[PDB]
Length: 75
Ligand SMILES: [Zn+2]
Ligand SMILES: [Zn+2]
Image (cartoon, rainbow, N blue to C red; front, side):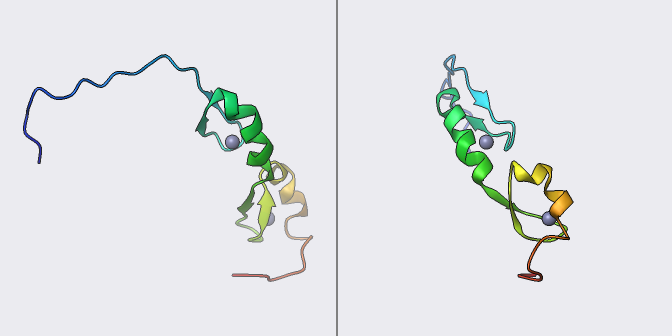
């Protein structure tokens, strides 16, 4: 596998990163604010109906989930 040699010394620098509240992913605090703008716009697959719904909408999606929608779009 790998010989037990001295080994390389891995070091880390002090970098303050910000985490999202919707996706909860690691991103640059600088590109965080913006990242959110799109983050929400993104649509995920629901389990009840099975349609693409906005991340931020998923909050109150359950309400319209089941009643709203053309019908059986996909399996
Ligand atoms: Zn995010
Ligand atoms: Zn749904």
